[PDB]
Image (cartoon, rainbow, N blue to C red; front, top):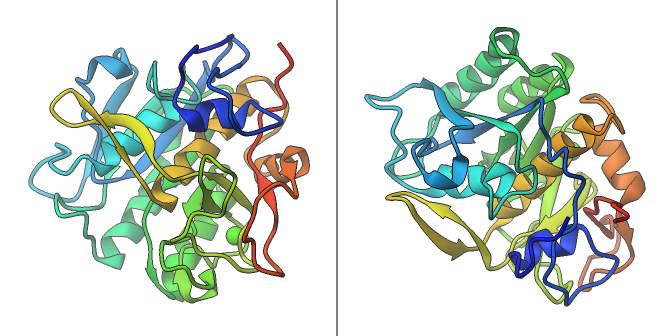
Length: 279
Ligand SMILES: [Ca+2]
């Protein structure tokens, strides 16, 4: 179904071309799947989440999202208006403080938490984790992301916003997870988007409207915004039975719009996330 006047990124992920504004998707909408948003938290009370979001873990004095970044990302995964998978269950894991910062040790603990926690949740169609965060290369951070993936979770991670090769960042550089670059509404690589061999896919990342704290909305940009498009897409596809956690990144690459993005450096995939939904 449509979304007439959907955010451009939603319309893009269900389209064979840029420049349209209706989002088309199977009504199953990720029902029975779960997506963990590992970030600054999620404002679960936001009407856009319809009771489908909840905080399950924090490493700080509160589970409240005092930043907005996590709420925005969660909105792109699964909010009613701004989300890819409009019926998924959203679980917030607050590894980032209200300034958007987090020690790698806390981020690692959060990933291992999700690998266990999914066994305490009802996700018959599958489990996804969205990591719109990163820093410099760390073998321990990469290994944590690898474990999470190995445990049966589709892990999607931001490539980073350095306009640089993502090989030097973590968890972006972990081969076994799905590393997500950002594009704009004109099918250009977003100017800040990292690139390189370690990228698996691109998603909408420039000027993305979604939920914000205080029951609000706003448009922001980043590989942080592209990542939840891919995470939501995975949840949606898993509900459809088209793929699994272990195979979703490959499946998304297999079925992506190919060769349509501009300013993709030689050696980086030219693949844009696409739901292949035929109304
Ligand atoms: Ca990767």
